[PDB]
Length: 49
Length: 47
Image (cartoon, rainbow over all chains, first blue to last red; front, side, top):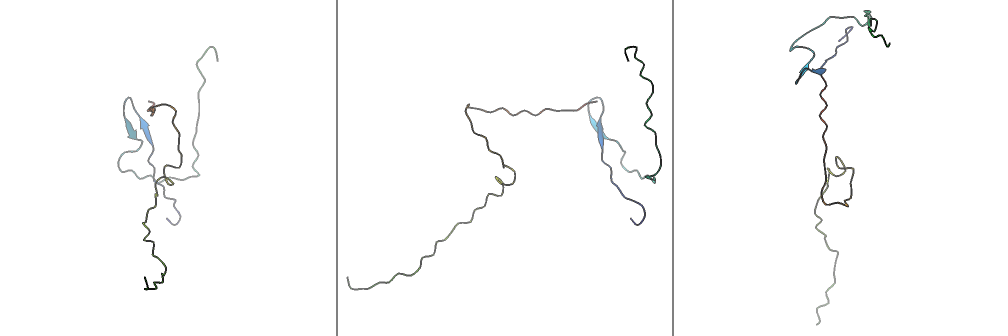
């Protein structure tokens, strides 16, 4: 769309017994692809580990 | 008897028929040895 990249997301997930889209009906997010996130994972609370 | 008939070419009247399904969705064929079949659909909905 000029400088901004346009996507349409439709991913779903299954709650207890039914499915549902991740997003509600009408959301619009201004974001930057270069923005840095964190996949951080804590320490496994397991004696065996 | 004495008519002297000469024959020309003969039109065929071909009948149009194209599957468009067996070669578009049913590309695979399986023979039978048994008398029935079983079809399994595995519903995977993890929470």
